[PDB]
Image 1 (cartoon, protein in one colour):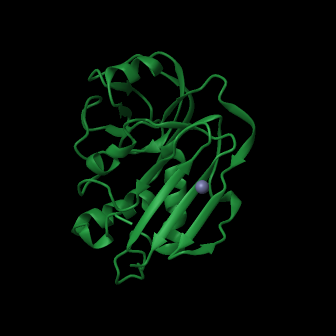
Image 2: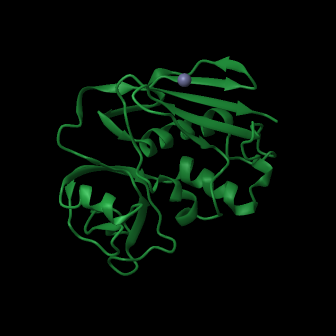
Image 3: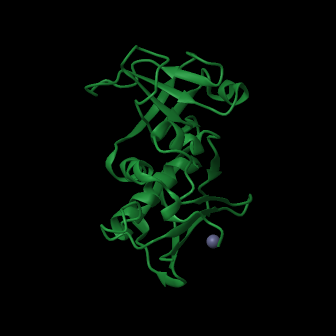
Length: 224
Ligand SMILES: [Zn+2]
C-alpha cells in the first residue's frame, strides 16, 4: 500500500499517460553516435529521424554532465518515448525530446531475444502473462524499454490509464523490476509528476540500466 490513487491524478494527466504508453510511437535505433550537445546534461542527435514527417533531430536529456560523458562519442542504441511539446535545442520547430533510453552498443547483443518473465497480481489473485509480452536484445537494458512494453500490456489487458467510465477498474498499481545482482527498481504506476510529457517522462532521466540476464518483473494491481 501507499501507492498513489488513480483519482489523485487530475484531468489531462491520465489521458497523457495513455497517450504515452499506448498511442504514441517510440524511438528505436541501433549503432548511433554523437558528440553534439545543447546543454551539458544532454546529447543532440541531428538527423535522428529520416522518414518522420515533422521531426528531424533528437535531444536526449540526462541526469548530469557525468552521465553524458559516458555515451558522448560512443556508439549507442536508443530505445524510448519522445515528445515535441516544450522541446527545443536542435533544428528549430523540428526537434523531439526524450529522457534516457541510451545504452552502449558494442558488446550488448544477445545471441537470442530474451523474454522477460512477468508475475502479475490483481487484488492478490495471480494472473498468467504470456512470455512474448516483454523482450529485449540487450545484455544491459534501460528500465524504460521494459517499462514501455509492460505498461502497454497493462493498457490493452486492463485499460490501465482509461477513465473509470471507459472500464478502468485498477485504482492503484506498482511495477517492480527485480534483479539478483542489485536492489529492485519499482514505479508507482500512478505516480508520474505533472500533466504533460516533458514532466511525466522525467522518470526515465536517470537512464537507469539493469542486467536482463536472469531477471523478472513483478506487477501488483488493485481495483481499490
Ligand atoms: Zn519478484
